[PDB]
Every structure is written in structure tokens, then in C-alpha cells.
Image: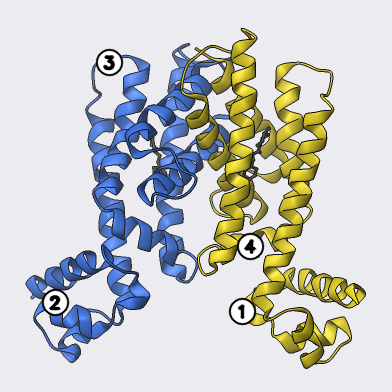
Chain colours: A yellow, B blue
């Protein structure tokens, strides 16, 4: 049932590792999943819907990991607190590079992919700002920029920098240096006057 | 001669203001430029080459403005020094939003557009790092992150944040707040321990 669904999704994630969605056919997904083409179309209307689902799963997985962290504070300095938070996204997206890369590209052509990405970005920005505000209310951070604006820029930094590193873009921060790079800019910009 | 060339480029920039390149035909560009379709193909092999040229012009214009600034230091504090530098890109790209938006999209489909963007990003990052290093050699900034890595992340931040603001993406920093937002993160991350 959804064993077939899960097989289709697993096949698609596997094939995206070697090639873009444009070079993957419904027939490729059916064959890998051990079903016919019409059987495929029972579970998904298009290969594009498969990618949307894969992205939805990855994004929700990151979001659920952040909710877990938010409910269960690590017992640590402010630097480590932000590092642990950024790390949810580094590891989650980092563990699904093909889906991340394909899903980012699909933002250009798919309103549903764009709206999905937008919804979660708003959520993560709102959460970032809430934490900055808490830190300001505690007297741990200075009241500099509007928190929501600072959060927006920091979140967009992370999007572009993590994804360029994962894709090995020229230029990009090496993947083994990206977490430390982002944490420094977050801590100095949130705590610095 | 290149009056016809300049007319084709001006027409394309105008039409990109109302619609994507995919909804602009060679015939639209010819007609706007006051020439026939075969006459068009004398100046450019495709509508895609027209966009490449427009982007090349905008990018080189920003780069020439930064070279000017680099040769002629504004007489001012470190915050204003970075603000003046970021502002070259805010105003240059900000004055050509349609070309900026279309050129960024074309990175996905055009190797020449990707390689153009990559070449200048490397250049601007190398320049950013050189300035950070100078500031460190002067004893004006602490030796924190590797300068080239810090420069990379800051430059990618600016790319994503400026372009999201210009496109009115959800989410995005409002255009009237983006310069101050980026300057704060640059100054605190370059000067902060
Ligand atoms: C509590 C914060 C921890 C840091 N954090 C992120 O890294 N940013 C979210 C982000 C946005 C785009 C792509 C990757 C990740 C947001 C929530
Ligand atoms: C001396 C610095 C001043 C600040 N600066 C920029 O804003 N970054 C370059 C950039 C990169 C992508 C898109 C827009 C602009 C780089 C050179």
C-alpha cells in the first residue's frame, strides 16, 4: 500500500543522487519501485509530485527535530545553543543532499514547492526572532536591529551558504567549515553592539 | 550598428520588467528594437544570449563601481566603509531588478550565466577577504574565522538577501531595511570576538 509509496519515494531519492529530475522518467521510478507505470500513477500524479513529497518529508523532519530541541534545552553557553540549532539543519538537509538540491531547483518551476519552502522559512524565522527577543528580554543580547529582520537575513544566509556547500558550488565554504562559519556570524551579530 | 545592439538590449530589459524571458520571443525583441527577426540573429544567436549580455553589463558595472571605490577610499569609520561598499551592489543591482532576477534564474539553465556569476563572486569574495586581512594586519579587527571563509558566507548572505528583497519574496527583508540589516551583520562579524 504505502509500502509501494515508500518504495517509489526511496527509488526517487536514490536516482536523484545520480541525475536531475528532468533525466528521471516515471518509467524509471516505476521500474525501481517494482510496479507498472499505471500503478505508479495511482500513488502520484507526476514525478514532480514525488519530489514535492520527498521535500515535504525532509523539511518536516528538520522542523520536528527543531521542535524537540526547543522543548529540551541543551545545557550550555549561548554559542553552543545556536550551534545545536543550526546543526539540526546541517545534519537533516546534509543527510538528504540530492532531495535538498532538487527541491531548491524546483522552487523556480513549482508553486507548491515554493509555497512549501516559504511556509517553513517563515516558521523558522519567526522562531529565530522569538529566541533573539527572549535573549534581549533576559539582558543577554543588546537591542540592535529589529529581531525579525536580523532573523530573516541570518536564515537566508544559512539557506544559501549551507546549500552552496552541499552542492560544492564555486564559490562555497567547505562543508567541514560551514557550521563553525555560520555559528560565528550568528553569535557576533546577535550578541554584538 | 551597435545602435541596433543597444536597442535590442534596451528592449529586452524593458520587456523583462513585465514578464520572464520564457514569455519573450525573438520576434518581440526584434519588433521592439525596430528590426526583423533575421536582422536580430545577426547581433545575437538567441534571446538567452541577450540576457547573458545584459547580465554581463550589470555585473561589470557593479565591479567597475567597486574598483572606483577601492582606488578612492571614503573618509569615514569602519561601519560607513562597509556600508559604502555593500551600497555599490544594492544600487547597481537595485537599479536593474528585472535583469538581476532573470539572470539569477538563468544560472540553473545556462552554463555561461553560472560561470559569469561564479567568476565575479570569486572576485568579490577575494576582495572582501583582502580587506578583512588588511583590517586584521592594522590591528582594527580580531583574528577569528579564516578571512576567506567569513567573506564567502557574508557574500552569499548578501546575494540571497538582496535578491530576495528586490524580488519581494516571502520571506524577505524589506528593501528600505536591507542595507542597514546587512551592514550590521558585516560589522559585528568582522570586528566582533
Ligand atoms: C533556532 C534556529 C536555528 C538556526 N536555523 C537555521 O539554520 N536556519 C534555518 C535554515 C533556513 C534555511 C535553510 C537551512 C536552515 C533556524 C532556527
Ligand atoms: C567590498 C565588498 C562590499 C560588499 N560586497 C557585497 O555586497 N557583496 C558582494 C555581493 C555578492 C552577491 C551579490 C551582491 C553583492 C562585496 C565587496
Whether residues under marks 4 and 2 lie with C-beta atoms below 8 angstroms apart, the answer is no
Which disc, if any, is residue B76?
3
Q: x%, y% of residue B61?
A: 24, 49
Q: x%, y% of residue A2?
A: 89, 73
Measured in 3D between alpha carbons, the distance from the residue under mark 3 to the one under mark 1, in whole angstroms, is 52 Å
Which marked residue is nearer to the observer: mark 4 or mark 3?
4
Rendered residue at 61%/57% (across/down): A116
Q: Which residue is mark 1?
A: A22
Mark nearer the N terminus (1 vs 4): 1
Mark 3 CB lies closer than 8 A to ligand 2: no
Q: Is residue B9 left or right of residue A44?
A: left
Rendered residue at 63%/39% (across/down): A124
Q: Which residue is mark 4?
A: A103
Whether residues under marks 1 and 4 lie with C-beta atoms below 8 angstroms apart, the answer is no
Which disc, if any, is residue B32?
2
Reply above or below: B185 against A140: below
SS class, disc 1:
helix
Chain under disc 2: B
Towards the viewer: A107 or A175: A107
Measured in 3D between alpha carbons, the distance from the residue under mark 4 to the one under mark 3, in whole angstroms, is 44 Å
Towards the viewer: A52 or B7: A52
Towards the viewer: B159 or A70: A70
Tags 1 and 4 both on a single chain:
yes
Amino acid at each position: 500500500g504505502d509500502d509501494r509509496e515508500l518504495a517509489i519515494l526511496a527509488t526517487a531519492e536514490n536516482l536523484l543522487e545520480d541525475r536531475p529530475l528532468a533525466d528521471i522518467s516515471v518509467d524509471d521510478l516505476a521500474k525501481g519501485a517494482g510496479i507498472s507505470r499505471p500503478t505508479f500513477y495511482f500513488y502520484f500524479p507526476s514525478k514532480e509530485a514525488v519530489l514535492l513529497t520527498l521535500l515535504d518529508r525532509v523539511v518536516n523532519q528538520a522542523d520536528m527535530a527543531l521542535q524537540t530541541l526547543a522543548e529540551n534545552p541543551a545545557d550550555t553557553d549561548r554559542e553552543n545553543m545556536w550551534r545545536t540549532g543550526i546543526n539540526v539543519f546541517f545534519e537533516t538537509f546534509g543527510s538528504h543532499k540530492a532531495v535538498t538540491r532538487a527541491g531548491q531547483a524546483a522552487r523556480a518551476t513549482s508553486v507548491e514547492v515554493a509555497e512549501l519552502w516559504s511556509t517553513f522559512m517563515q516558521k523558522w524565522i519567526a522562531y529565530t526572532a522569538a529566541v533573539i527577543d527572549a535573549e534581549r528580554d533576559r539582558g543577554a543580547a543588546p537591542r540592535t536591529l529589529p529581531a525579525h529582520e536580523l532573523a530573516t537575513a541570518l536564515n537566508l544566509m544559512n539557506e544559501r551558504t549551507l546549500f552552496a556547500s552541499f552542492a560544492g558550488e564555486q564559490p562555497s565554504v567547505p562543508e567541514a567549515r560551514v557550521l563553525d562559519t555560520l555559528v560565528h556570524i550568528w553569535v557576533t551579530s546577535i550578541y554584538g553592539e
